[PDB]
Every structure is written in structure tokens, then in C-alpha cells.
């Protein structure tokens, strides 16, 4: 009957407070610590996401991979008024669970969910959705999409000097082609944020890669 993702949403609805994003996040973290593991970024990596958002105060943020809306809630709740999160999610079941999670949280007006493959959607952003340049991108979808989408974002002109890329899972499962590129290119300046895989004692980390402009 129910899926794991419907079980996570259900647990939130019964146990957290509506319109309160912090109870929504703590509820998801509790469910995933005691009942079923799921691929949410988690609290430890979440605090690194908090700080990054706090440091740069981004007006437009793009999230690749929504899943259950845990990072969406995590970032949306910290945005200054007027700022927006676009999130791209290729699975409609996840897209639907994400929407409802944001509604419960009362953050639905700060988020625009686009249901489709990011490689089809990134090229449409300027024309269809009015975009100039992104101030921040958060990558947490399929690990083989990080590099081709980072290059498609450049190709398309969605990046600007000072745009922050924040990439989950750079140690485990790992994102080798992406990590070696951004660390090797003069078009980015990178910092590694060592941490733990969500709900586990296994060493993971995030990578922050700030776009310096096109290479000469
Ligand atoms: C060793 C080891 C292996 C695996 C793990 C476990 C583990 C730990 C983690 O933190 C992880 O982030 C992952 C992981 O694979 N995440 C993939 C995330 C997919 C979501 O994004 C969606 N999506 C996938 N491609 C696209 C796309 N083009 N455009 C739009 N949405 C897309 C999907 O529809 C899902 O909503 C796995 C831990 C340790
Ligand atoms: Cl998440
Ligand atoms: Cl955690
Ligand atoms: Mg992840």
C-alpha cells in the first residue's frame, strides 16, 4: 500500500506542528533514526547547508533532486523575504510528497517545484521562468548528473562570478568526475566540508565550489 516516502510524510503530519519548519525537519530525522533509513541530507550535513545559506543570503536558489522535500524545507526556511527556491524533481511521486511537505511547513510560497529531468529543465530557465543568474545551486540528485548539469548551467549562462555550488555525497556514494573537475578548474574555488552520511557513522562530506567566471 504505502511507500517509504508516504510513511515519512504521514509521520510528519501526525508528529510535527503545521507552519513550523523546525518540527518538520526534527520529525523526519526522528523517523529516519528509529524506523527506516532514507536518503535525506540529515541534520549534520543540514547544519552545513544552514551556514552556507546564512553566509551568502541567496536571492535565487536552485535545488537538483527534491526527494521528500527535506533540503527544500531546510533551505526555504532560512531565505530572506522575496528570495525563491526552484526545485527540480524527475519523479512525480516525490514531487507530490515534496509539495505537501512544504504546505505542511507553510513555505510553499517560497518554492517552485518543476516536475522533470533537470537536463531538460535547466535550458528552459531563462526564457520560460524569467531567470538571469543563479546565486546558489544545491546538487543532491543522481551522482552521474552533477558534472553534465554543472557544465550545462555554464553553457546556458545561469552562473555568475560568486555563484555557490553545494554538492552532497562527494565521498559516499561519491561524485568522482564532478569533484576532480571543480577542484581542477580555475573556473571554481572549492572548500570541502567533512561530515557523516545521513543517519550513519560513515564519513561523508559536502563540497562548496564558488564559480569564478569563464576560463580564458
Ligand atoms: C556507499 C553508499 C551508497 C549509497 C548511499 C545512499 C545515498 C545517500 C545520499 O545522500 C544520496 O543523495 C543518495 C542518492 O543516490 N541520491 C539520488 C537522488 C535522487 C533524487 O533526485 C531525483 N532525480 C534523479 N535524477 C534527477 C534529474 N536528472 N532531475 C531531477 N530530479 C532527479 C530522484 O527522483 C530522487 O528524488 C544515496 C550511501 C552510501
Ligand atoms: Cl533531502
Ligand atoms: Cl544526521
Ligand atoms: Mg544525498
Image (cartoon, grey):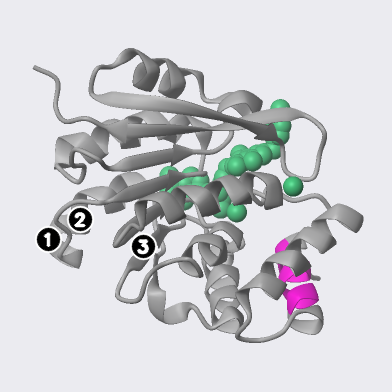
**Does residue 4 lie above or below 199 as drawn?**
below
Q: CA distance from mark 3 to mark 1?
A: 15 Å
Q: Position of residue 129 (x, y in %)?
A: 20, 66
Quickly name the residue at label 2. Answer: 124
Callouts 2 and 1 close, C-beta under 8 Å: yes
Work out whether residue 16 can be spotted.
yes
Quickly name the residue at label 3. Answer: 86
Q: Position of residue 44 (x, y in %)?
A: 69, 46
Task: Name the chief secondary structure element in magenta.
Answer: helix
Q: Position of residue 106 (x, y in %)?
A: 53, 83
Q: Of discs 3 and 1, which sits in the foreground?
A: 3
Q: CA distance from mark 3 to mark 2?
A: 13 Å
Q: Is residue 107 left or right of residue 88?
A: right
Q: Is residue 124 magenta?
A: no
- The range drawn in magenta is 5-12
Name the residue: 74% across, 75% down: 12
Q: Nearer the viewer, residue 11 or 89?
A: 11
Work out whether residue 3 can be spotted.
no
- How many C-alpha atoms fall within 10 Å of the one at disc 3: few (<14), some, or many (≥20)? many
Name the residue: 19% across, 46% down: 158
Q: Position of residue 28 (x, y in %)?
A: 74, 64
Name the residue: 59% across, 33% down: 169
Amino acid at each position: 500500500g504505502d511507500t517509504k516516502e508516504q510513511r515519512i510524510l504521514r509521520y510528519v503530519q501526525q508528529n510535527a506542528k503545521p507552519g513550523d519548519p523546525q518540527s518538520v525537519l526534527e520529525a523526519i530525522d526522528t523517523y529516519c533514526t528509529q524506523k527506516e533509513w532514507a536518503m535525506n541530507v540529515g541534520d549534520a550535513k543540514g547544519q552545513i547547508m544552514d551556514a552556507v545559506i546564512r553566509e551568502y543570503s541567496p536571492s535565487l536558489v536552485l535545488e537538483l533532486g527534491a526527494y521528500c522535500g527535506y533540503s527544500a524545507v531546510r533551505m526555504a526556511r532560512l531565505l530572506q523575504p522575496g528570495a525563491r527556491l526552484l526545485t527540480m524533481e524527475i519523479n512525480p511521486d516525490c514531487a507530490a510528497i515534496t509539495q505537501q511537505m512544504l504546505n505542511f511547513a507553510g513555505l510553499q510560497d517560497k518554492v517552485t517545484i518543476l516536475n522533470g529531468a533537470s537536463q531538460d529543465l535547466i535550458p528552459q530557465l531563462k526564457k520560460k521562468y524569467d531567470v538571469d543568474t543563479l546565486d546558489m545551486v544545491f546538487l543532491d540528485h543522481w551522482k552521474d548528473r552533477y558534472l553534465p548539469d554543472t557544465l550545462l548551467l555554464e553553457k546556458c549562462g545561469l552562473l555568475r562570478k560568486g555563484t555557490v555550488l553545494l554538492a552532497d555525497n562527494v565521498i559516499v556514494p561519491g561524485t568522482p568526475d564532478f569533484l576532480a573537475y571543480v577542484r581542477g578548474s580555475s573556473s571554481f574555488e572549492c572548500t570541502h566540508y567533512s561530515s557523516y552520511l545521513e543517519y550513519m557513522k560513515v564519513v561523508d562530506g559536502l563540497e562548496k565550489a564558488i564559480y569564478q567566471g569563464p576560463s580564458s
